[PDB]
Image 1 (cartoon, one colour):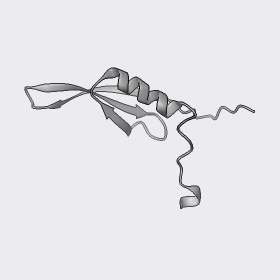
Image 2 (cartoon, one colour):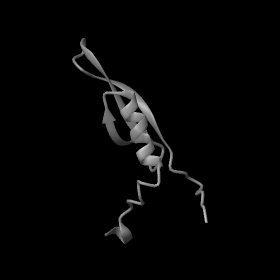
Image 3 (tube, one colour):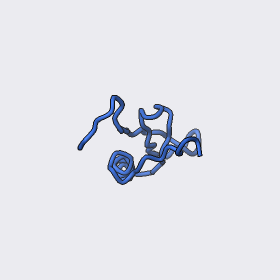
Image 4 (cartoon, helix red, strand yellow):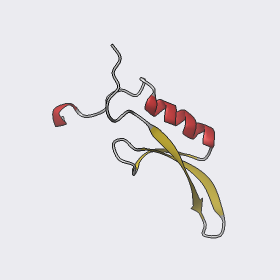
Length: 71
């Protein structure tokens, strides 16, 4: 019994810069189209942590975290 919803659990990575206006540092933000494309999950200074975190969001290990009946 497998099931694929009309809106699958998919995420992506966004490369940003932080720090001083002249001296910037490279950062990676994990964001997902679900439930909203502005939903930031986690931030990491390395690409690998972003890809790994992306798997943590898309793998069955991340359970349905929607609060039961608004509880």
